[PDB]
Amino acid sequence: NAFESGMLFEQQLIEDESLLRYQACADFWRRHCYPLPREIAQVVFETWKGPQALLRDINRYLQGEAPVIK
Amino acid sequence: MLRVYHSNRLDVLEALMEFIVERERLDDPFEPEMILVQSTGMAQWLQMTLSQKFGIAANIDFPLPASFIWDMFVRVLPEIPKESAFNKQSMSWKLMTLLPQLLEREDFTLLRHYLTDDSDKRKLF
């Protein structure tokens, strides 16, 4: 059932969703942490240093269905 | 007139066609003997077997069936072009031309709601 679903006819299949995840998280850390002043960025630096440290504590939340935040 | 020979094995029919050539040779010795096969493997096998059996080869040609039928058309009927105007790429590019005109004719509603969302011609191709 192709037309009403919206599928392409040949699919280059991949299964390694970690490298793209880290590469894209690097861009978010690049564009949403850089232009902060130091007096604000100190508290951000205190909790976690870099994107590699940040991804370890949020990797399991991203997979599958996105949850609902209280 | 038409002939049909059922077969269990193939070498006996190879001997049968060899016998046919033996009992009757073509009146024009330069006339090519058309032989139809469905595979290049069978083509090479017939080449090697017939060359080994006769010692040599004599006016042997192996065209694929569609090419043979086209060769029959071009000699039986006039005005026929040498090759078709309808090939698997020609319809592809012509449908590339003709789909955008025929969008929204009240019959292609599913095609419109699938294709017109967002694309860079890949889905259209």
Image (cartoon, grey):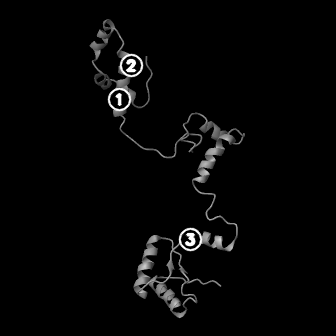
Q: Residues within 10 Å of mark 1 (few under 14, many from 20)?
A: few
* Residue at the image position 38 percent from the left and 17 percent from the top: A32
Picture coordinates of residue B30, whole percent (x, y): 54, 84
* Residue at the image position 58 percent from the left and 68 percent from the top: B66
In the image, B80 versus A13, the foreground residue is B80
Q: Secondary structure under badge 1?
A: helix
Measured Cα–Cα span from mark 3 to mark 2: 64 Å
Quarter of the rendering occupied by the N terminus of chain A: top right
Q: Which residue is mark 1?
A: A23
Question: Is residue B3 positioned above or below A31 on the image?
Answer: below
* Residue at the image position 45 percent from the left and 21 percent from the top: A68
Q: Residues within 10 Å of mark 3 (few under 14, many from 20)?
A: few
Question: Is residue B108 positioned above or below A40 on the image?
Answer: below
Given the current orientation, which residue lies at the most extreme bottom position?
A: B23
Picture coordinates of residue B11, whole percent (x, y): 44, 84
Q: Secondary structure under badge 2?
A: helix
Picture coordinates of residue B75, whole percent (x, y): 65, 73
Question: Which image quadrant is residue B27 in?
Answer: bottom right
Q: Which residue is mark 2?
A: A31
Q: How many marks?
A: 3
